Amino acid sequence: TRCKLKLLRMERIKDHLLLEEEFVSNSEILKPFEKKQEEEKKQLEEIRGNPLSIGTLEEIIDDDHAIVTSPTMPDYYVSILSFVDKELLEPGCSVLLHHKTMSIVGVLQDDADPMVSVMKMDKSPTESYSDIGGLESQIQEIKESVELPLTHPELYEEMGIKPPKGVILYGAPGTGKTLLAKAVANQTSATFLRIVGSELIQKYLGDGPRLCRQIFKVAGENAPSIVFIDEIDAIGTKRYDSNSGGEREIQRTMLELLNQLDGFDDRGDVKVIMATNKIETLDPALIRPGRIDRKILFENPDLSTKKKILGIHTSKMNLSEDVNLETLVTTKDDLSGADIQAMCTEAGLLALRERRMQVTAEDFKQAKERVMKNKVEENLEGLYL
Amino acid sequence: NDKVRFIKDELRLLQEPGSYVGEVIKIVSDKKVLVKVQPEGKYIVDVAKDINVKDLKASQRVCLRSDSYMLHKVLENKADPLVSLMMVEKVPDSTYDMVGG
Amino acid sequence: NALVDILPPDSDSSISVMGENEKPDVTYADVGGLDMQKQEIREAVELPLVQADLYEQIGIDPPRGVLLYGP
Amino acid sequence: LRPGRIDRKIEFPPPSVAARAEILRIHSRKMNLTRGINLRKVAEKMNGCSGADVKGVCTEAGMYALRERRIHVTQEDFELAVGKVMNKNQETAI
Amino acid sequence: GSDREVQRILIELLTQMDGFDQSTNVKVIMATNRADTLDPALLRPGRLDRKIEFPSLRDRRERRLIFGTIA
Ligand SMILES: Nc1ncnc2c1ncn2[C@@H]1O[C@H](COP(=O)(O)OP(=O)(O)OP(=O)(O)O)[C@@H](O)[C@H]1O
Ligand SMILES: Nc1ncnc2c1ncn2[C@@H]1O[C@H](COP(=O)(O)OP(=O)(O)OP(=O)(O)O)[C@@H](O)[C@H]1O
Ligand SMILES: [Mg+2]
């Protein structure tokens, strides 16, 4: 408070003074700016004038010439003049052309695209680690692969071992595969690209690889980056039948994803999170240990663990003193953590239909009973015993 | 008098340099605007000194005077994409009283 | 490109009103069955032109555009 | 259908004989009437299954008004309409 | 390019189909022998409204009627 304002007050009037000194004594000397400066800006503007025609640099020839394509049809063998970085002009780049006699007078253009914005999450999830009730061991296999080499890159470089690459979070539904991704995406504050696996099937032919080549290029540019692929199970199992390339198409796209993930490229820093619920379907080439390094696995929360999960959802909630948290845990016998969240949400909704702020013991008992009936047991382990 | 001063001088105004209609794609902080004349490509061109670049914003149909294509004025009508998709589907407004049953 | 004058609304039409003598020879007499269809389309196309008033009075929306599908 | 994924599930039964009467009245407010017509008795007689069908009884009644050049939607028109709408629906639905 | 030019023709038709309202004009009457390929943006209400059916099946009465007029 006292000292931060006090040092800023000295720095910001000392900055003022130095900028005045540089401005006065570089205007009276003609070798620096002065005479060249007041004529180049006015000339550069005036000579080329307007309209500046945008075009696309089709290709560049090493001799400061180029072949540029106007949308109006005529192509041109132009020259590359003043005020352009000649290494920045490459195929695909958009250039501004001098309309009287076609020469590249520069590129001033950001070229912002909806292709980079669609991958990008401006995420601010209220979730932080330790909104995961228990399953503490699993959290600390994920943080050692993704988050920790950004905090302390010292440990892996002292040891001499290359950081582990890639993870797959799989298990039963409701164990928080998505909830862990959100915790670890919040801390790192790396570029977090998100792309659901369903999107990689689209109707046209051969578009699958173009879409898959695009995602990883945005990521490699934005290192350090995370690419979370949600339910990559979806492309194997389903058959939307919009894509008229059939199953042959889905296979050729898959092979593209395999090359972008390691292959020949030698990309920058790109961690990958691959969430799935059924690892069987997934092509054995993808899961192969070399592209992914650690296969984290989850299981159905226990009776001791479910107390921790319940404590998180019941804290935010307002309660009467008549509630007993312990009788809601024991009745359910092996029910995931997704159901516990819905059981709290359902109770607060019953109390809001009765229009009383408190969530009493009865709203909990009606909600818990309704949620057990909605479920559907598991005829996988019923077969068994 | 307003009439006859206008008729005689009207012949010299009708040898117009023409005009064009573009649309603001995006602006930049050199006081210049990227506008698309529809049949052709796009052009980066500056505003006349009098209007501002603050007046101009997302997808305003703009006037141009064909010579340097100088932007002259915002046009009454705007073109916005989200209104046009809900218009072509065509769903008529309803009320709780119509549903009743 | 100054707008020096106007033209009529009937003019500068690529495709003009036929019927002078190109009107086809078929009539309701040559047509046979499909009696349900004849009645529908006469109610859809013919009755609104001759009598607009009937539709407003009764308070039904007039059938506007007509579509014909079939194999 | 997992717990917590949606939040509410609405079911719509086909309209009862009580509901049909209300729904048939909302469409009848737009067009003429005649004293003494019981919009309730036409809903019962119509077996039906949809409110789409119900709206078609009103439009078809207006078609029978044009052919005779009536001045008002009368009790005879609904009895003819019910039939035309029900017979057309049963030939395509069976 | 070919597709991008048809989209313009199809937008105009839809726009002026709602402008036709409150004229003596009866809207466009149009036929197609295909029904699966139609754009459903035409068959929304307020544009094309009435759908005519032409059957392929002929019962015994309706068949004699067609034979009668040709013969
Ligand atoms: N271990 C857990 N601790 C606390 N809350 C949990 C846990 N697991 C799930 N939840 C709650 O359930 C909600 C939904 O969970 P989530 O979307 O992660 O399920 P999932 O297992 O990813 O489902 P899917 O099989 O569809 O991927 C979370 O937002 C969270 O509130
Ligand atoms: N009800 C009928 N009475 C008399 N002749 C008929 C009848 N129906 C069809 N025809 C005969 O069949 C011919 C074929 O009819 P038309 O060419 O109009 O069929 P369409 O529905 O236009 O077929 P398309 O799908 O090729 O357009 C008619 O020119 C007519 O001679
Ligand atoms: Mg999930």
Image (cartoon, coloured by chain):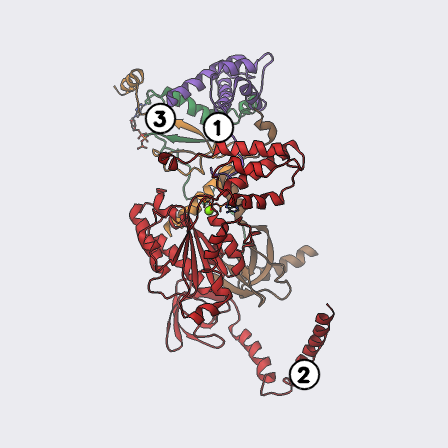
Chain colours: A red, B brown, C green, D purple, E orange
Q: Secondary structure at mark 1?
A: loop
- The structure residue drawn at horizontal position 65% and vertical position 86%, both measured from the top left corner, is A25
Q: Residue furthest left?
A: E71
- Measuring from the top left, give residue A128's x and y in whole percent: 55, 54
- Measuring from the top left, give residue D54's x and y in whole percent: 50, 22
| D30 or C13: nearer the viewer | D30
Do tag 2 and tag 3 residues touch (Cβ < 8 Å)?
A: no
Q: Quadrant of residue A377?
A: top left
| B34 or A128: nearer the viewer | A128
Q: Which numbered tag is attached to residue A21? A: 2
- The structure residue drawn at horizontal position 43% and vertical position 60%, both measured from the top left corner, is A271
Split into quadrants, the picture shows ligand 2 in the one at top left
Q: Is residue A71 visible?
A: no
- The residue under label 1 is C63
- Measuring from the top left, give residue A125's x and y in whole percent: 55, 52
Q: Does label 3 lie on the same chain as label 2?
A: no
Q: Is residue E59 visible?
A: yes
